[PDB]
Image (cartoon, rainbow over all chains, first blue to last red; front, top):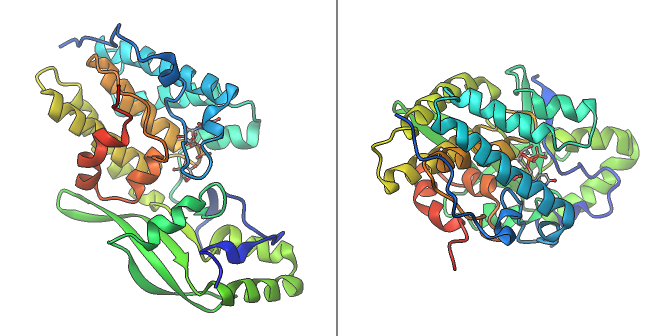
Length: 25
Length: 294
Ligand SMILES: O=c1ccn([C@@H]2O[C@H](COP(=O)(O)OP(=O)(O)O)[C@@H](O)[C@H]2O)c(=O)[nH]1
């Protein structure tokens, strides 16, 4: 099994690593 | 009563240039740079200049101090107005804040999973489905009431993911899968509900007001500095730059009493250490997140 997180390899859809803000649901 | 003010016995430059660094245990390359030493020395210098004014009665409230931190930090942005706005705006209670645990935050995944206080939980996802997550739930205690803070989550059936993510991508589009992972990454920090920040902010003026005593011993001062650091960093009051501001403020109060804290140790990112601990834990571990070696 992959490292924690490393399931997210070469995914163009990988989030960017900084704080994002979103409207509450 | 007035206070000593910043010391004249300054840290060696090599240490100035590491004030407010983010010395990741997985990439202290950025700590060594010309720009980042430039950034850090500037913070060093503007902390003392805030230092100067706490001593004189100039800065009356933690919010005023936080302003000085914000003014400093903004003048270091060479970025523009979306980004400027963020570093300058408090988080508003109609939003949530989220940090995905991708680079440069990978060192954190381990910190959550081997964390004594971690739970094992189930996190129910619209695209991936159900997930086992290791979960650290930072909580403060204030007045005796419990205030949830930041919630770390690391997804742990990794094989299933890389499969399922790859699967999910092609249908909705990376476009539509990115969307999801910006906000719902299996591995992520969910930050303090912006709703708690008025009462935290009140709490911080209380601490600030206390720590600009004259009568306090060295111990009880450092305690009150670690705390102020602890609360401000963990509340994350602003959309961006909270870590920088927390450290700046925590240090400005130090200098107002004539203390000269050293950089933080390597691999010891101050706001993460704070986020991943409870208050009294952090207060007691504080002096040693600091590089206090001659
Ligand atoms: O060019 C920079 C910008 C920031 N930092 C530090 O790295 C952390 C980044 O957090 P900050 O709150 O500045 O911004 P954000 O994390 O929201 O991007 C803080 O400890 C900053 O002092 C740094 O070393 N160099």
